[PDB]
């Protein structure tokens, strides 16, 4: 925000050396601050690229810097029958430079190591190394935790177990406050990634020149994994340190694996012993999630937070559905050991192929606002595609999406400005942290110095109403009575290390809206509608207040009376003097407007005394935790007293509430306007009720309030409502409090199905039939203590009609049957049968945790028993399976309210290739007998009659 | 009625026409007491004033050039014209939207050129043996679809740089596979060998002369080869008048951008071709891998269709990549690469069975909305692509363009192009927000109070405040104040406490945070909803406090989306037919279903439950609900009469259908992983022989008749 983009400092190195690839700050014993810059491609003595490190002293004009001296010659040693060789050509020394106390660690990831023994060898691979330098005592040491004397044949015979030949140690380095250097090796364990931890003191005290291979007693490394997810994961691309377990003794590490889980990315938080405390997964394929990691306390709660980057993230645009812009994820550490959830904030870039988020650098309290800030670099962002750096300021809820300041790249195209960033250090000793940005393409480092921040508080005071009848003042140089009133302007400047001499220009304008010639109120002194003053606030901790007199013109000179008189005060810095270079940055309340008016229709007393009454009601009372709760507040306001001046409605909402919409039933062309702002910590919504609102006015407002996630608000939430009026008497109405209770409720759905729904058996192992049961937690809340029972006919015996082969549970539920199912190993008119009548087999499943949106599946396989199929094959067979589940409690403070129940029944019907059941020929026989009897009687009729 | 033209206007032709899409201006002199010149055309016509001077611009969609769609492409392919119209011109008045329609067709036979890009890692060695005689087979199989075919070959292993190479011992440089006693070529990044040629024998000759290299890292850098093949059009020779196919065969993972840090490469990749006369990637060791965004951009620019013919072990990864890059198809390649021919043959139809549309050179000023028309008159709102097509099928797309104001350019042009096709529609838009009468100018006219003002289209606009109807009230003049002309429905503050009552009208003031307009200074900007640092959701412009949505959006905040592209499943039905799509998200009305498209339901009735109607016509050519034409309207499955009854279909299960004949018809449903659902139905189902009583009763009655005849003849003799 307060960074100066005009007066920078440029440090340059040898051309074509990639100066500025990595950089850091260094503090000597006297407190002097210098810069350490690594140039991986510096030419060595043998006219070959070997890298180097430069210790730039702090100079305002910058320029060339001296270079620290490191050994750049190949080492060949003979021990026993083995020959150890080190190759430093194109080692890229300085790719990652860190400083701790009085030690500078510069690493060459691409240094090559080899071992020769007769014919076999360990192969020449880029093990990498790190050189530690102590300039004060002029001491040198080396550290290479991935040097071994194992031949390639042994690794081949062991399936490449514990293969550290491709560590590339030094890709990312970090030194803890205790003094334990940690180095990342993405290529270790055959492109799986690893970490190497070692104290600096042990490294210094355990180094003997000429001994290429040695072991540090306190050295520790991460372990290998066989999970296919870690394959080609590059676990160690970025490494950071922080506190996450709540105990100050242990130090937690954050390790990035951009290519984890098939190019998905991950960030793992581990303890000191390399135990996975947490894992954060990526969002999109090939997004390189985890390229850069940073740890800082943005919210100021005292608990470290996490920042992750994904340069290759692709967003959605109308022109093209995929646009590589990159992204940054902010995760906030919650209270307690609760696991980190979804990203707290998402930041997206604008320029295409900008690689936004490739470098995240903490800056501390840059503006001394009590909250930490950060800087995010896009190497190839901006309209011209030359690079940008965006400064994000912190707040109570986290970070601000809008970037406070954007710094461009003075270097030309291809400079990769912003590739390496570093801050949170004061180099000019002005009380504010500075920033350093490298650019290896142009081979230059740019230093930005923070400027003091001055906060301005402006207040304007004036009488609520004016009565032209009363005249007390007299115009200068004459004897003309005229009414007058006092206007008071208070301006105060605050900050840290602000200049001793400070001047601010304050401009006061009266009745700004009206034309200059048509102004109604004019200053008594100069008889002018506007004035300007130069206040010297330098060193004046208390605000400076000034007072002036303003008089109202004669009634004949103007005819407008109802229009309010508006007064504006504007505070600004002095115009740029010789040399430009403004000393400080001013922000805050630099413009304040206050409105008065002429007395009218206030009665004989000439003083308006409004009386305001407010009533509030709430609809949507049931608040469900973890749901898009939308309450509706209906407020009716009336003014039984005199007209209220500048009457507004103030509605203080809880922490998680928000404002969406508001309507006014009264009038259809009123154009209600409401605004929402965070005064200190609460989201106050101000709705305009009316300037001198008329007598007995009654206004009804219906507003929608969206209550966000709430897990600690308690049993009920509180909304406050009041009326704000500028009138001297009864400035506000009665305070209204609405208490909305909160209850937690969740619904669980059980659904059952059978495959195939319809089966036909013709006339060993018979046809396959499976029953599936699913539990779905559609409810917004969370349910624990889930217990389910599935009841099936039979007991898995040869006599049983159906035989259960296997039951597969999915979703983590733990299931056990009774009696045991599948005794044999087995290497392979409707009739109702159910657990109620036939023998019952019950399988019980348990789930202690069932989060929102999770689904649990239980499948059971079986086959109709052919020996039992053959017997009585002429009877239709419908089988039924039953389920019964319920939960114990919920993980929420609010006890209410029991629930949920469940009853699922699954049916399956079987058919045959037509049944041989006795066809109802009985009816045919009865009909034939009846016809025969009728014929016999008919014949006998005329037989006996004749 | 007052409408919205009469109010919030009546200042000049420009603003008057710029208020609402339907307003008219009466330039010809008439009575000025009727509040004329800003109202509906009907009101002006009722008030006359139409002596060829009425100003009322209307949007037009005149077609400049249009040609009929060709039927077959065999010769003179320069004028196939498979997309019509080719170029149209649109003229839109400010804040007005106009619609047009286009048609897309595949012209039967169309020339095809295929470039074969195959990895040459050690594990691929055996595969190289199965391709030595692929050119002739490919030509024979493809001759049934394309009469003009060209084929090509390519290779790629990885970046020749440590740790990807075996730098030591030195013998490994010219023979990395020396430990296993084998001969191999040095590592290379991309080696083009055969250009696209119509001589089939060249493909066979070039193959079997290649070899296989070796590397250390499992992932293979194939994206570099893909990008080099795409960008280097001249080196390999893509043909602009033919359909492009790029087969990418691999059996391992693929590198992405920022993976070159291990080898020291940090320079971002660029799409410029880097293939010299030696036919090799010169910048392989000095250029980083390309990102997916650049790959997709350069693949769409050159109109190249991509086929990921990958082994089963990494099929999921390339399926996940495929849904990102448009116009890409995935396929399973056998371990010996013996399924490549059929894979490419079917992938050709698969890719040509899909039509999409992309917009290029679209300025931010205007927005487009799309409707699609699949086969038959059915229309799917908010969709720019239709699935389930075939060769020769014609589809229609309705495109509605809406603008915001009139940009100060007056000449814009964009293009709508189907993926993988040269032909495209070029749409030229010219904005006309200026009235013709303004050309008269007359900057100084005596009617404007003796030549101290400007006259325009029948109204005098004068000075810095002179606004009287006769250009006489001035700014400081009109000191006496009249009534019943500054506030509506007297009883409210004048000018809504925002403006000054001068000249008899409310002149709005305080031009801060935007502009304020209105006959009573009630409408204004900077008074609308703010979603995230943007007004009216940042999509549409809000007028008079209403967040007027732009195209592709509809809502109070104008955040809800109308286009339904994301909520379309792979079965050709919106949200898999188990739910609706709202604001780009599928809501599953049917219980027990979840997912992005409501497709992953585990507890739904099997497919055969609703397939009874589909199989009716195939086996009987009759059945209920035949009026709806259910034979082929929703089920694309193919029915085949096979009595094999022993297929080992993993993703298949037998089921039964019940007929009025009371005979169970058992049939198989196979849902192949390729999406080619197939039904196997047994013809003439065996109905058990039930009726056997008719013969018995006939014999019984015959015996009774014989007995009766015997009795009759006995009586006759007696
Ligand atoms: C592409 O896809 C979109 C999305 O569905 C289609 O938009 C739909 O277009 C239909 C046809 O234009 C709309 O149907 C109706 O059309 C009315 C305009 O036409 C009027 O017709 C009456 C008939 O008596 C005439 O008197 C008038 O003079 C007009 O000519 C629409 O205004 C109307 O929509 C309603 O309007 C009322 C009043 O304005 C609204 O209060 C109401 O909310 C609704 O908008 C009616 O529906 C259809 O509405 C519209 N879909 C919408 C607006 O969501 C395109 O037509 C498709 N493209 C093509 C080429 O067909
Ligand atoms: C078009 O607009 C312009 C301003 O943009 C008008 O200019 C000024 O208009 C006012 C109108 O009130 C003039 O004032 C009026 O003038 C009369 C006449 O006085 C004259 O004075 C000149 C000397 O200056 C003599 O030579 C003449 O014979 C005559 O006596 C006077 O009685 C009042 O003061 C009255 O208000 C003003 O004079 C004029 N500006 C100038 C420089 O002359 C302009 O008039 C207007 N066109 C019109 C109204 O036709
Ligand atoms: C909800 O789930 C709980 C599981 O935690 C069920 O607990 C069981 O509750 C019954 C009360 O009906 C306890 O008594 C049992 O009653 C049956 C007759 O219904 C009887 O046959 C048993 O011998 C037993 O006495 C039962 O002990 C208890 N289970 C355990 C392990 O303690 C509860 O029933 C479920 N409620 C509903 C409504 O489903
Ligand atoms: C390629 O695409 C597949 C399919 O979209 C993706 O795999 C899916 O990854 C998600 C990751 O969130 C899995 O969800 C998780 O599954 C685990 C069990 O593995 C479960 O414990 C979690 O609660 C969560 O539900 C999802 O199951 C998985 N599905 C499949 C079919 O794999 C992924 O994007 C890519 N997978 C590859 C390349 O293997
Ligand atoms: C969408 O385009 C169609 C086709 O141009 C328009 O339909 C025609 O509209 C004109 C003008 O109203 C009529 O004269 C024609 O008879 C219509 N033809 C058909 C086939 O409907 C339609 O009006 C356009 N819709 C919009 C909203 O612009
Ligand atoms: C004593 C003697 C004469 C009695 C003979 C009874 C005769 C009339 C009976 C015996 C069997 C009968 C038939 C049996 C079955 C059918 C099929 C039916 O779809 C139409 C009627 C029809 C064709 C019947 C017609 C009447 C029938 C021919
Ligand atoms: C081949 C079979 C069916 C032949 C059986 C012969 C029958 C028709 C004979 C056996 C006995 C006979 C009956 C014997 C006696 C009498 C009494 C006489 O006053 C009238 C005839 C009458 C009633 C006869 C009718 C015919 C009769 C019923
Ligand atoms: C050397 O430095 C100059 C400084 O301007 C630069 O222009 C040039 O590119 C560098 N390299 C060579 C080879 O000169
Ligand atoms: C570690 O824990 C011990 C015992 O609780 C405590 O005395 C010590 O201060 C802790 N270390 C810290 C806080 O650094
Ligand atoms: C009022 O102050 C703002 C900054 O708060 C400034 O930009 C503006 O120029 C000032 N107005 C005038 C008239 O100087
Ligand atoms: C906001 O709340 C804090 C609580 O610590 C309080 O100190 C501060 O004064 C409040 N702000 C205002 C404007 O009252
Ligand atoms: C627009 O804003 C919300 C919040 O981001 C978004 O989720 C949704 O699509 C829109 N709002 C509503 C109410 O639909
Ligand atoms: C059908 O049943 C047979 C058993 O005879 C089985 O082999 C087959 O997999 C089942 N499914 C299909 C589609 O045939
Ligand atoms: Ca700890
Ligand atoms: Ca925190
Ligand atoms: Ca801050
Ligand atoms: Ca500083
Ligand atoms: Ca009073
Ligand atoms: Ca193979
Ligand atoms: Ca490789
Ligand atoms: Mg390989």
Image (cartoon, helix red, strand yellow):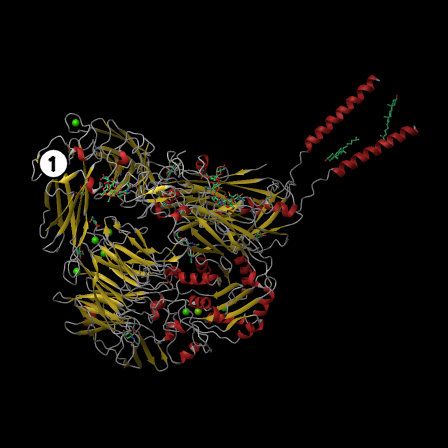
Question: Position of A30 compared to B63: left or right?
Answer: left
Instruction: Name, please, the residue furthest toward the right.
Output: B717
Q: Position of residue B546 (x, y in %)?
A: 35, 41
Q: Secondary structure at mark 1?
A: strand
Q: Nearer the viewer, residue B592 or B655?
A: B592
Instruction: Name, please, the residue furthest toward the top.
Output: A945
Up-down relation of residue A237 to residue A617 (above or below): below
Q: Position of residue A832 (x, y in %)?
A: 54, 38
The quadrant where residue A458 appears:
top left
Up-down relation of residue A597 to residue A24 (above or below): above
- Callout 1: CB less than 8 Å from ligand 18: no
Q: Which residue is mark 1?
A: A484
Up-down relation of residue A406 to residue B475 (above or below): below
Answer whether residue A840 is visible to the viewer in this image. Answer: yes
The quadrant where residue A562 appears:
top left
Answer whether residue A864 is visible to the viewer in this image. Answer: no
Q: Nearer the viewer, residue B432 or A149?
A: B432
Q: Position of residue B494 (x, y in %)?
A: 27, 34
Ligand 17's quadrant: bottom left
Q: Position of residue B408 (x, y in %)?
A: 37, 52
């Amino acid at each position: 925000l307060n960074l100066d983009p005009v007066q920078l400092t440029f440090y340059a190195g040898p051309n074509g050396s990639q100066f500025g690839f990595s950089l850091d700050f260094h503090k000597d014993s006297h407190g002097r601050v210098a810069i350490v810059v690594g140039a991986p491609r510096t030419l060595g003595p043998s006219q070959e690229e070997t890298g180097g490190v430069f210790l730039c002293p702090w100079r305002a004009e910058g320029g060339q810097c001296p270079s620290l001296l490191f050994d750049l010659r190949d080492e060949t040693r003979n021990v026993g029958s083995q020959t150890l060789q080190t190759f430093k050509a194109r080692q890229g020394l300085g790719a990652s430079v860190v400083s701790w106390s009085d030690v500078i660690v510069a690493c060459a990831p691409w240094q090559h190591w080899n071992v020769l023994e007769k014919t076999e060898e360990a192969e020449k691979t880029p093990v990498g190394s790190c050189f530690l330098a102590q300039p004060e005592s002029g001491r040198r040491a080396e550290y290479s935790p991935c040097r071994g004397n194992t031949l390639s044949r042994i690794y081949v015979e062991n399936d490449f177990s514990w293969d550290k030949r491709y560590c590339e140690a030094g890709f990312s380095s970090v030194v803890t406050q205790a003094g334990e250097l940690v180095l990342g090796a993405p290529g270790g364990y055959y492109f799986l990634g690893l970490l190497a931890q070692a104290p600096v003191a042990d490294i210094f005290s355990s180094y003997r020149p000429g001994i290429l291979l040695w072991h540090v007693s306190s050295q520790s490394l991460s372990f290998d994994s066989s999970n296919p997810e870690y394959f080609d994961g590059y676990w160690g691309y970025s490494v950071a340190v922080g506190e996450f377990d709540g105990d100050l003794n242990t130090t937690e590490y954050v390790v990035g694996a951009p290519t984890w889980s098939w190019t998905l990315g991950a960030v793992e938080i581990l303890d000191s012993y390399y135990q996975r405390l947490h894992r954060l997964r990526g969002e999109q394929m090939a997004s390189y999630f985890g390229h850069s990691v940073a740890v800082t306390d943005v919210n100021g709660d005292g608990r470290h937070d996490l920042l992750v980057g994904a340069p290759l993230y692709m967003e959605s645009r109308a022109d093209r559905k995929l646009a590589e812009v990159g992204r940054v994820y902010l995760f906030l550490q919650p209270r307690g050991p609760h696991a980190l959830g979804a990203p707290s904030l998402l930041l997206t870039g604008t320029q295409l192929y900008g690689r936004f988020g490739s470098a995240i650098a903490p800056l501390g309290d840059l503006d001394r606002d009590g909250y930490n800030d950060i800087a995010v670099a896009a190497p190839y962002g901006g309209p011209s595609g030359r690079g940008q750096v965006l400064v994000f300021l912190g707040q109570s809820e986290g970070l601000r999406s809008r970037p406070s300041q954007v710094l461009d790249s003075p270097f030309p195209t291809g400079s990769a400005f912003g590739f390496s960033l570093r801050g949170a250090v004061d180099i000019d000793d002005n009380g504010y942290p500075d920033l350093i940005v490298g650019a290896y393409g142009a081979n230059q480092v740019a230093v930005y110095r923070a400027q003091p921040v001055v906060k301005a508080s402006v207040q304007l005071l004036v009488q609520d109403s004016l009565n032209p009848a009363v005249k007390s003042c007299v115009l200068p140089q004459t004897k003309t009575p005229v009414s007058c009133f006092n206007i008071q302007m208070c301006v105060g400047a605050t900050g840290h290390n602000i200049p001793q001499k400070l001047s601010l220009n304050a401009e006061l304008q009266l009745d700004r809206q009206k034309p200059r010639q048509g102004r109604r109120v004019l200053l008594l002194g100069s008889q002018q509608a506007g004035t300007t003053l130069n206040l010297d606030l330098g060193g004046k901790h208390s605000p400076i207040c000034h007072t002036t007199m303003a008089f109202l013109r004669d009634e004949a000179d103007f005819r407008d009376k109802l229009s309010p008189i508006v007064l504006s005060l504007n505070v600004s810095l002095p115009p740029t003097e010789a040399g430009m270079a403004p000393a400080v940055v001013l922000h805050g309340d630099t413009h304040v407007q206050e409105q008065t008016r002429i007395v009218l229709d206030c009665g004989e007393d000439d003083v308006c005394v409004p009386q305001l009454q407010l009533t509030a009601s709430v609809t949507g009372s049931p608040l469900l935790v973890g749901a898009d709760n939308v309450l509706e507040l209906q407020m009716d306001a009336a003014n039984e007293g005199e007209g209220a001046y500048e009457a507004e409605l103030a509605v203080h909402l809880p922490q998680g509430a928000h404002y969406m919409r508001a309507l006014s039933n009264v009038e259809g062309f009123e154009r209600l306007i409401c605004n929402q702002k965070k005064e200190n910590e609460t989201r106050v919504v101000l709705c305009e009720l009316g300037n001198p609102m008329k007598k007995n006015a009654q206004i009804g407002i219906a507003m929608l309030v969206s209550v966000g996630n709430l897990e600690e608000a308690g049993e009920s939430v509180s909304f406050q409502l009041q009326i704000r009026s500028k009138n001297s008497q009864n400035p506000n109405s009665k305070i209204v409090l609405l208490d909305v209770p909160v209850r937690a409720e969740a619904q669980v759905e059980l659904r059952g199905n059978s495959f195939p729904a319809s089966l036909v058996v013709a006339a060993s192992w018979g046809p396959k039939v499976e029953h599936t049961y699913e539990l779905h937690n559609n409810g917004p809340g969370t349910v624990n203590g889930l217990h389910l029972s599935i009841h099936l006919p039979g007991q898995s015996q040869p006599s049983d009609l159906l035989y259960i082969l296997d039951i597969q549970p999915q979703g983590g539920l733990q299931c056990f049957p009774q009696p045991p199912v599948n005794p044999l190993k087995v290497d392979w008119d409707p009739v109702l049968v159910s657990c109620d009548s036939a023998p019952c087999t019950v399988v019980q499943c348990d789930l202690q945790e069932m989060a929102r949106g999770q689904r649990a599946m239980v499948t059971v396989l079986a086959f109709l028993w052919l020996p039992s199929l053959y017997q009585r094959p002429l009877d239709q067979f419908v089988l039924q399976s039953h389920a019964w589940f319920n939960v114990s409690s919920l993980p929420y403070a609010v006890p209410p309210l029991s629930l949920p129940r469940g009853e699922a029944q699954v049916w399956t019907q079987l058919l045959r290739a037509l049944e041989e059941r006795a066809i109802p020929i009985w009816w045919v026989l009865v009909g034939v007998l009846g016809g025969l009897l009728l014929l016999t009687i008919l014949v006998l009729a005329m037989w006996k009659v004749g | 009625g007052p409408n919205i033209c009469t109010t919030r206007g009546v200042s000049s032709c420009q603003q008057c026409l710029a208020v609402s899409p339907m307003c008219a201006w009466c330039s010809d002199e008439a009575l000025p007491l009727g509040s004329p010149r800003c109202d509906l055309k009907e009101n002006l016509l009722k008030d006359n004033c139409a002596p060829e001077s009425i100003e009322f611009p209307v949007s037009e969609a005149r077609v400049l050039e249009d040609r009929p769609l060709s039927d077959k492409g065999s010769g003179d392919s320069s004028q196939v014209t498979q997309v019509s119209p080719q170029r149209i011109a649109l003229r839109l008045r400010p804040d007005d939207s106009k619609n047009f329609s286009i048609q897309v067709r595949q012209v039967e036979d169309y020339p095809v050129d295929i470039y074969y890009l195959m990895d040459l890692s050690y594990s691929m060695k055996d595969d190289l043996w199965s391709i030595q005689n692929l050119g002739t087979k490919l030509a024979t199989q493809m001759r049934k679809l394309t009469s003009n075919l060209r084929i090509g070959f390519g290779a790629f292993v990885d970046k020749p740089v440590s740790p990807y190479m075996y730098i030591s011992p030195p013998e490994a440089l010219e023979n990395p596979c020396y430990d296993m006693k084998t001969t191999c070529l040095p590592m290379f990044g991309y080696k083009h060998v055969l250009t696209l040629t119509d001589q089939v024998t060249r493909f066979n000759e070039e193959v079997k002369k290649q070899s296989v290299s070796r590397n250390r890292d499992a992932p293979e850098g194939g994206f570099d080869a893909i990008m080099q093949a795409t960008v280097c059009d001249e080196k390999i020779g893509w043909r602009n008048d033919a359909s492009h196919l790029l087969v990418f065969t691999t059996d391992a993972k693929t590198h992405i951008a920022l993976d070159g840090r291990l080898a020291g490469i940090v320079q971002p990749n660029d799409g410029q071709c880097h293939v010299g006369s030696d036919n090799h990637y010169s910048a392989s060791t000095t250029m980083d891998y390309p990102s997916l965004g650049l790959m997709t951009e350069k693949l769409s620019q050159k109109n190249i269709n991509l086929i990921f013919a990958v082994t089963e072990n990494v099929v999921n990864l390339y399926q996940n990549y495929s849904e990102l890059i448009p116009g890409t198809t995935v396929g399973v390649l056998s371990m010996d690469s013996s399924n490549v021919l059929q894979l490419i043959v079917d992938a050709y139809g698969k890719i040509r069975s899909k039509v999409e549309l992309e917009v290029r050179d679209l300025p931010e000023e205007l927005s487009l909305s799309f409707n699609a028309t699949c086969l038959n008159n059915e229309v799917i709102p908010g969709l720019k692509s239709c699935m389930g097509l075939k060769i020769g099928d014609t589809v229609s797309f309705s495109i509605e363009a809406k603008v915001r104001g009139c940009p100060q350019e007056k000449e814009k042009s964009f293009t709508i192009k189907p993926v993988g096709f040269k032909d495209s529609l070029i749409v030229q838009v010219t904005f006309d927000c200026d009235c013709a009468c303004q050309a008269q100018a007359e900057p100084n006219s005596h009617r404007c109070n003796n030549g101290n003002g400007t006259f325009e289209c029948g109204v005098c606009r004068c000075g810095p405040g002179w606004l009287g109807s006769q250009c006489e009230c001035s700014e400081e003049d009109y000191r006496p104040s009249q009534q019943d002309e500054c506030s509506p429905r007297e009883g409210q503050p004048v000018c809504s406490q925002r403006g000054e009552c001068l000249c008899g009208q409310c002149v709005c003031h305080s031009s801060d945070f935007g502009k304020i307009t209105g006959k009573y200074c009630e409408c204004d900007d900077f008074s609308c909803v703010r979603y995230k640092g943007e007004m009216c959701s940042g999509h549409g412009q809000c007028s008079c406090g209403d967040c007027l949505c732009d195209s592709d959006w509809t809502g109070y905040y104008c955040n809800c989306t109308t286009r339904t592209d994301t909520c379309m499943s792979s079965n050709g039905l919106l949200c898999s037919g188990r739910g609706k799509c709202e604001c780009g998200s599928c809501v599953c009305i049917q219980p027990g279903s979840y997912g992005d498209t409501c497709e992953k339901c585990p507890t739904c009735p099997d497919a055969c439950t609703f397939k009874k109607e589909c199989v009716e016509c195939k086996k009987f050519d009759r059945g209920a609900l035949h009026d709806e034409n259910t034979c082929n309207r929703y089920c694309r499955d193919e029915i085949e009469s096979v009595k094999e009854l022993k297929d080992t279909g993993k993703d298949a299960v037998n089921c039964t259908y019940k007929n009025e004949d009371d005979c169970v018809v058992r049939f198989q449903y196979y849902e192949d992983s390729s999406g080619k659902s197939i039904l196997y139905v047994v013809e003439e189902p065996e109905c058990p022989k039930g009726p056997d009583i008719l013969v018995v009763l006939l014999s019984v009655m015959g015996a009774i008749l014989l007995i009766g005849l015997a009795a009759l003849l006995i009586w006759k003799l007696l």
